[PDB]
Image (cartoon, coloured by chain):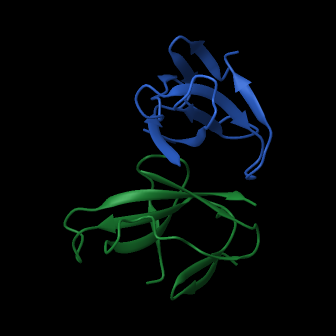
Chain colours: A green, B blue
Amino acid sequence: ECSLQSCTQHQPYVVDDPCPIHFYSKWYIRVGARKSAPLIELCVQYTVSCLPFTINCQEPKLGSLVVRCSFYEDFLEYHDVRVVLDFI
Amino acid sequence: ECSLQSCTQHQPYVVDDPCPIHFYSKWYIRVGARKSAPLIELCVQYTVSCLPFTINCQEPKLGSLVVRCSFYEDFLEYHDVRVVLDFI
């Protein structure tokens, strides 16, 4: 799955949670455009705040933002959602 | 809306139509990561075939592939869907 979000470049932006309502959230940065790339977990200048998760509206330099969604709190099954931005 | 498709880099790939079933299709290349960017219409080396629409599995150099979907043949209302690839 994939999420297209619009924001103003180089300005704070509260990222809309692409996961279904109630689903638990983990935010990552992947490396390269490659299917199985390593992930850098966020909230364990790009990152602005973690409460709520807000960023400066640009693409990170080494990968593309990713949200890990799960129906369960400890992620028995999870689904990833790439977050791609375009600039108004 | 957005579509994440997996393919093998630098190899022919038949793009899966992200539009709903039956919806009419126009394929474009936008310019830059900017919301209102000009569009280059395809099927009026990246492009491999138009029947069915197949490409070489990479990101185009100046923008990101886009599909224009419409319930009507002459596009009274249309919805765009960005196509983003990752590489297995």
Q: Using the image as rendered, state which of residue B77 and residue A22 is in the foreground.
A: B77
Q: In this figure, what is the number of numbered marks?
A: 0
> Residue A37, position in %: x, y?
45, 54
Q: Is residue A84 left or right of residue B52?
A: right
The residue drawn where x is 44% and y is 65% is: A67
Q: Whole-percent x and y of residue B43?
A: 66, 16
Residue at 76% of width from left, 71% of height from top?
A: A10
Does residue A62 appear left or right of residue B88 in this picture? right
Residue at 22% across, 62% down: A77
Q: Give the residue at the far bottom of this rendering.
A: A51
Vertically, is B7 above or below A16? above
* Whether residue A30 is situated above or below residue A21 in the rendered picture: above
Residue extending furthest toward the left? A76
Task: Tell me which corner region of the image, top left, top right, bottom left or bottom right, holds residue A4.
Answer: bottom right
Looking at the picture, does residue B62 appear above or below residue A6? above
Q: Where is residue A52 in the image (x, y as percent from the top left)?
A: 52, 85
Residue B77: which quarter of the image? top right
> Within the image, what quadrant is residue B50 found in?
top right
Q: Position of residue A82 (x, y in %)?
A: 48, 56
| Quadrant showing the C terminus of chain B | top left
